[PDB]
Image (cartoon, coloured by chain):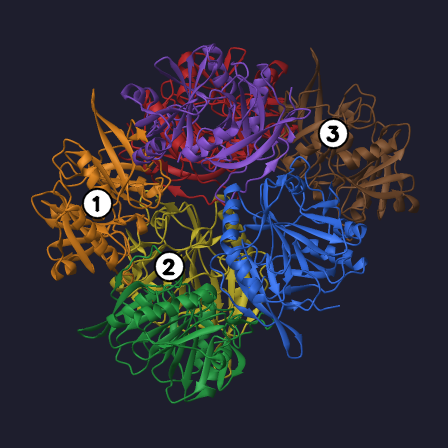
Chain colours: A orange, B purple, C red, D brown, E blue, F yellow, G green
Amino acid sequence: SIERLGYLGFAVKDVPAWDHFLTKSVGLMAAGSAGDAALYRADQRAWRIAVQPGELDDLAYAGLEVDDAAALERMADKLRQAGVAFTRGDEALMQQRKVMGLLCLQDPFGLPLEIYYGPAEIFHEPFLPSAPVSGFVTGDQGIGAFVRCVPDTAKAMAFYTEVLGFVLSDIIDIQMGPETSVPAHFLHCNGRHHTIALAAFPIPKRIHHFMLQANTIDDVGYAFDRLDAAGRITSLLGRHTNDQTLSFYADTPSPMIEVEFGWGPRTVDSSWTVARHSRTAMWGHKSV
Amino acid sequence: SIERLGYLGFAVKDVPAWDHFLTKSVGLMAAGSAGDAALYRADQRAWRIAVQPGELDDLAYAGLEVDDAAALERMADKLRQAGVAFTRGDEALMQQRKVMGLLCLQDPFGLPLEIYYGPAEIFHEPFLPSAPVSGFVTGDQGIGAFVRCVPDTAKAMAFYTEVLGFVLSDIIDIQMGPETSVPAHFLHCNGRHHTIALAAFPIPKRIHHFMLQANTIDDVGYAFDRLDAAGRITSLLGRHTNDQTLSFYADTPSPMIEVEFGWGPRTVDSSWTVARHSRTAMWGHKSV
Amino acid sequence: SIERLGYLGFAVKDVPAWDHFLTKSVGLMAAGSAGDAALYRADQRAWRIAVQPGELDDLAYAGLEVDDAAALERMADKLRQAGVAFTRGDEALMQQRKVMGLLCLQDPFGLPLEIYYGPAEIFHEPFLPSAPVSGFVTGDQGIGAFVRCVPDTAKAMAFYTEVLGFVLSDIIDIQMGPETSVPAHFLHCNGRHHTIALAAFPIPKRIHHFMLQANTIDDVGYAFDRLDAAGRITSLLGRHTNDQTLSFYADTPSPMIEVEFGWGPRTVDSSWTVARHSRTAMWGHKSV
Amino acid sequence: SIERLGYLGFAVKDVPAWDHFLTKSVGLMAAGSAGDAALYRADQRAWRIAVQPGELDDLAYAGLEVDDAAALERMADKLRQAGVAFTRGDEALMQQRKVMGLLCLQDPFGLPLEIYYGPAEIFHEPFLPSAPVSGFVTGDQGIGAFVRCVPDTAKAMAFYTEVLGFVLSDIIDIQMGPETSVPAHFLHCNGRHHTIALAAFPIPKRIHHFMLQANTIDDVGYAFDRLDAAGRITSLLGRHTNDQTLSFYADTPSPMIEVEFGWGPRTVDSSWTVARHSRTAMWGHKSV
Amino acid sequence: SIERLGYLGFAVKDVPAWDHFLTKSVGLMAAGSAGDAALYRADQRAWRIAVQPGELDDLAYAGLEVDDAAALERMADKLRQAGVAFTRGDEALMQQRKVMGLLCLQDPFGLPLEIYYGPAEIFHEPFLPSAPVSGFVTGDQGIGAFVRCVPDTAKAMAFYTEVLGFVLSDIIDIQMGPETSVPAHFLHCNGRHHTIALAAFPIPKRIHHFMLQANTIDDVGYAFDRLDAAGRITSLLGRHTNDQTLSFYADTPSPMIEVEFGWGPRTVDSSWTVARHSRTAMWGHKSV
Amino acid sequence: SIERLGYLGFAVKDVPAWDHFLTKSVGLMAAGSAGDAALYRADQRAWRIAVQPGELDDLAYAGLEVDDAAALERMADKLRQAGVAFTRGDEALMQQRKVMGLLCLQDPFGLPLEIYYGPAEIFHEPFLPSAPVSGFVTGDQGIGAFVRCVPDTAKAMAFYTEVLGFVLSDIIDIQMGPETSVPAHFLHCNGRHHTIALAAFPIPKRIHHFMLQANTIDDVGYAFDRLDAAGRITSLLGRHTNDQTLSFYADTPSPMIEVEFGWGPRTVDSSWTVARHSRTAMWGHKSV
Amino acid sequence: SIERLGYLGFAVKDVPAWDHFLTKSVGLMAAGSAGDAALYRADQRAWRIAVQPGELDDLAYAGLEVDDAAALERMADKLRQAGVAFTRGDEALMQQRKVMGLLCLQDPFGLPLEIYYGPAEIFHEPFLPSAPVSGFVTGDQGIGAFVRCVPDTAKAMAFYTEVLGFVLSDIIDIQMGPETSVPAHFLHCNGRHHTIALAAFPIPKRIHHFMLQANTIDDVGYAFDRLDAAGRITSLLGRHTNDQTLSFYADTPSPMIEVEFGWGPRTVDSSWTVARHSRTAMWGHKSV
């Protein structure tokens, strides 16, 4: 099974705006380029987020990491047995993403996924944030999480759990209208409460948002002000019911895609009980 | 196997007396109603104890929790293989108990059991006790425990262990008369020393008592005085030989059903050795 | 010297609104009455805040605590030597405030102060909050703090430091207009970063606000939502530069008097260096 | 000033009953005799409690310890300056109490006090309790405490504080009748919340009770049962408002003198604030 | 497999001498009798060592504990499969040893073994040592250990490992004469470095010695002096190479059987590497 | 007495080279300018190091901090009593250094010193290093230290100790030639092993070097490589005998002035014993 | 699978130079001889490194340890199944290496390997270093590591992983020339980041170097100076990218074989992710 979410690639209309957003606002470290993709770091990895020009203004691919070569062949076997089409990344792609091997596939609704092993680390170029952020919580929990929009949550659930090995943490019924709610399913594949959530939102984007976790509450507080100065805040500070991440939300430069910048969630394990929540926020998160 | 005891429902003759008892005396939080049942909370769960009108003046049902949907189907399989009759809770029942799925059955002596998964949590309405109690120890150990009266301990034991997956912790020989004792069997299904004890007491009730565990010794001390002011104390403070819960006992408003309010027990695991004790109390617990 | 701020008395136009505000919103425990004053508790003390009817809609008095009878006589000596008028609280007043002895005086600008020793504690009636708040940080640091408006900060400073024994922690230049700032002086008399701050604000009230410190960040988060539901929020969540209290502000029912509800500040001692800050907030606290 | 209470001597009508009481019930170690006094140990000291035959059935003397020879001469100087009569213990007395030097005096109401230094320790005969008690909390806090009955609390207070250097911790108003209470004053001379309390009780004895502090709550629980088997319990388990000792009370064999056997109190220091309490118990301690 | 050594029974010529030895010297608690056996306690168990009259002056039986009824049936199955004769303890024997079930067998060289489950605990009669010893280390590691003399170590090894499930920890070559050594094999069945050691010593007894582990180094030091006063010391204080127990040895009243009284050994687990040592002592243990 | 070294000002020939050196190499944060001085930060202070153009290529002034206004007047009194000339910084100077008050003087050999209180902090502009350094150890220990060259160590010693209140930590005899050594005296004024060392080196500069302390050993390791890439290393990694700072040395752009970048020293207090060392390095620090 | 590297044997041209090197420089304890091999200790083992005369001037054999006799037979089975030739060490060899059993084989490129169990420990002759080194980190992680030169890394990898059970930790691309790098594969068999690394270096030796890990950073610092005094340093202090060992390198007396003396690495487990690094050093390690 997938061990963690390791990287994200966005294809966007305003590369400079994304560059400023990820560095001066979010605090990531600019790390050069690979092909037409600008690269950004959050830790020791050669890169975590890639930004390339494109009309999509959306997530273009997600990297799903495994721990070694044999694990990757086992994922190939799982894909074959499940009838899921995939191709093996060629040398150029391997070089482009800085990995030792990868399988290219899509989820049932067209999001390209890349299952890989052997990513590049560059400890000789220690991480230096572009804005005051003490650091990000990554490690075995990967880069963070994202909320995947899908037209059929049950169909998406079967794929992510049965094929990729993610596990359901819990569900939140997100009230949309007076008598309309959407059951968001939160899935884990390691200690991070969730790495991918699945929801049938009426949004045209592949994802609703991606989440990064910072080391301290002040990191979050300071980041709020930077995004507020940029005019991008979409939520006040708040804390989620299920993972208890204390965060705020802001718009990325791609319309309808937000970022969640947070701190201090609960983590999970094999004893996590599936439960249901009627609200996204235990406190705060008022929409603005 | 069952992971924990999650809820209890009582059917009683004096609903107002039970309401005052659970709130002003015990300290639980009133949490509205579902159908004709008044609901009470001890933590983040939407409810833990339900009280409905009825002539039984007894425990009407017990909710036995599992961690996910697949676990529930596996319990269904265990019931089928064991020849234990059960039905699937319909939508109305699921809505009534605020769960995602449930199986309805009885133990061999008529106590209705509900095996469920996916309970509702309401972190946006943080727990507020009705009396000075710092909190209850629940979490993975469930709401607490109860002592189930049975006519045939061996028969009850086979069902709870072989069918439901509980495990024997230890036995106490409870001296009843000059040359008469009853062997109480204490069963666990998680870290709580026991969740269900089985005993052939000559009492007309389904249970002898239910137990709640508070966070501090002062919680217990203060609760003693509140129940004493109410004229309900049945035991002085004391500590059990087997789980070493330091507690007192009091009458509930239903005759012959008591409550045990305690603190600081030992917890168990796979290395817990079956042992036998000749007394219920290491110290205290004098009957009054 | 004064050891800590122990109590506050308000004289207000809307006693019921203050009652609801302190209980359902802030979380204090209603504790009966003394004379025409409604009493509120935050801990083991018989009372911490008193609310009496009056047109002032302001702080009517502040209780400044010392540790014993001899300390009180020494404060009397300090007042005499400094030429500050004072009277000794009579039996009725002692009974009213539940103290063993008190001196009644005013600060140079008319705020009545009561220096006392021997307050009443009622551990047999353990604290029970009226809203979900885990508890307040009081103890040797007293009930909290307040910001005292004065027409002459230097004059006020001499009195609070030379006569009462408070000590300057630091200064914040609070920008009021384009080319106008007010130098707020923050004074301590124990580990609390400040107990009284002195500022020449153009506000008609004796105080700008009073501050209570809760045990957890969630206490603060939950309280924000309760005050927001009441329509009283005046600041978003934020953190101060000098004491690093993470808080929000809200209006009390008395116009121009606010409450600050906070968590997690730095504490001080004899090694605290006087420093100057150009902003009140390290992050957040946007005015709304 | 006095550093700690080091020993107590009782003169009683039933020496065998006291012997059984201190050993089999309380758990002290029999330690032979000195003259006509039977000796009992609680720790490394050669003795802590002495029992001699006499019609008093009361406390005959209390040993007040200082840390060295010079400290004792300084106490002599304090007594001289205060006009308090005293004599120097002769060689026989020094040998009898196993000390290097002592001053013999009385408090203003006739209780003999012995101020001493240089007590004997016998680590080569390690402490062995006579009943199951894990140990007593003594050390720098001395053997324990006692409540001294006096006809004039103010007079007693001046002596214990001004002459002997004890310090007021707090006061409890002990309700005796419908409209009658006695203000008990609790005095410390080290970390123990109090070593001597002063109260104008209408009891014919020099003391109301003496208190010993055990290491664990189980020590207390087990001791309760032993004293209950002996028919001596006078209070149920409970916890005091001021020192928060969790204890029970029992009769000694001398009528109107009780023992308090407790655990887990708060300790004090130079920052302890004088406060007043309206009840002796935060919870429990119901009289039986 | 066997979980721990739970009890030992000796058959001796001088019951009074053994009684004094186990109580006044070793510190065990006398606990009455069962049949013609005097019982001794080291902890919460109703008994740990039994002493009965007999000419053997040797270990008469050893109790090997398992955690539950099913485990005992599994041991029965192992014995059957291995062709090892055994009988089921009858009611009288079960009553005599205070257990819920037992299998009676012998090791290949005639030492009676009793495999049992469900021992009696008596927490209402808390442990009280007969001599100054703070306590013994037992719990999941059982009562202690013994060194079993055998004529054929390989044969004994096969039985204890293959049949009973003990595991080899390490070996010490014990030099007997100028060119003669005996390879002692140390076996564990839990965290205790060893519970049974196997050695081909030329001693007529079933065992060379049994070992008890005390809580502190002072326990050991004080015990040394008590056994020295009794004229029983056989070794000076020392520390073993393999388990690093710091101990001394003394004679029991049965000739050629000693006791080892120790403290502070290393404990083991599944990662313990088999190693060989050329000496029994890292330091000390000089024979006297 | 002086509490800590708070700031340093350099007057240099190559401002751009110093700018690159302090930011890209050392890791300090550029913080704008005040007058013709470029400012650099290491923490929450508005500035720590100032660089202005000048032919000196040397330390132009050192800021010595005290905790409050009264402390500054007391230093003025000490200067007056000692006959040391000083002037009071005017408004322009106060504005320039961002302090509430300052005294301007020189040490006996012409180094300008500024004794000040009330420095500016800017927590709303959190520290962001210009190179990968996790942070600096400052706080109550000030910015760091420097080694002051003097022609007469005894004369310098009398001034720094008797007038400014520094305290001798220890001495190192620094071997210069075959039969020539210089006794460097290391002085503290807080927990930092030394803040100023005094040595009669034959160097034309006011100081031999200044020292900054980083949070981790990796900070130091990474910094070494950055300075090595710049061609500035003067010592290999090493650790001092007296403070046990683990550091390396590098040239600043001003000839004969170096920087020491270190980690992990011992800290001092009132119990630090004056001792003498024959070498500067316990290990390493080979000159290159 | 192999549990750890337990010993190394070198065959060298200058035995005295190796003797001085391992004792006076590295700090190992001389431990006599076995046959023509001089023995050296690093801990409780009778020996860790053996040095015998020979023209090879290279590693002559490596001892690979397993935990018991059965484990060794299982390794024999693995060798048989894989078609790898091996012989059983005879009595003389067993005596020579001080082990209870061993299999002699070679890796695919001629390095003799000895798989063994039951090594000799000599706690009665406690370790005494020959130079100031506080101790070495060995225990379950074995003596240390070595870098094995091979002509075919894939072939070597298959043998060490598939046959011996080592596991790939990570890879470093070691740049040799302008457009030439060698992919070093680092393998673990316990918590030590690696025990054997495999690399196709163009060196005539079996190994590039062996590594020892000392307890403290000062151990490393002091050792650097000792090797520098000997003229043997080949690298400055530095820290590796992958295991983060902070070390230096020095020449052994055998040309082209070095020693790495280090401290403070990361350790591994089953969750270690295979990653790739482009440099050997995160910082330092400049070649000299």
Asked if residue F47 is positioned above or below residue G228 in the image, the reply reads above
Amino acid carrying label 1: it is Val
Asked if residue A85 is positioned above or below residue G78 in the image, the reply reads above
**SS under mark 3:** helix
**SS under mark 2:** loop
Residue sitting farthest toward the left: A55
The mark found on residue D227 in the picture is: 3
According to the image, label 1 marks what residue? A163
* Closer to the eye: label 1 or 3: 1
Asked if residue E177 is positioned above or below residue D248 in the image, the reply reads below
Residue E142 visible (yes or no) = no
Q: State the separation of the CA atoms marked 1 and 2.
A: 29 Å
**Quarter of the rendering occupied by the C terminus of chain G:** bottom left
Q: Residues within 10 Å of mark 2 (few under 14, many from 20)?
A: some
According to the image, label 2 marks what residue? G268
Horizontal placement of G83 versus E60: left or right?
Answer: left
Q: Residues within 10 Å of mark 3 (few under 14, many from 20)?
A: many
**Quarter of the rendering occupied by the N terminus of chain G:** bottom left
Q: Residue at x 47, y 57 (%)?
A: E270
Q: State the separation of the CA atoms marked 3 and 2.
A: 58 Å
Amino acid carrying label 3: it is Leu
**SS under mark 1:** helix
- Residue D107 vs residue B175, the one in the foreground: B175
Residue D32: quarter of image: top right
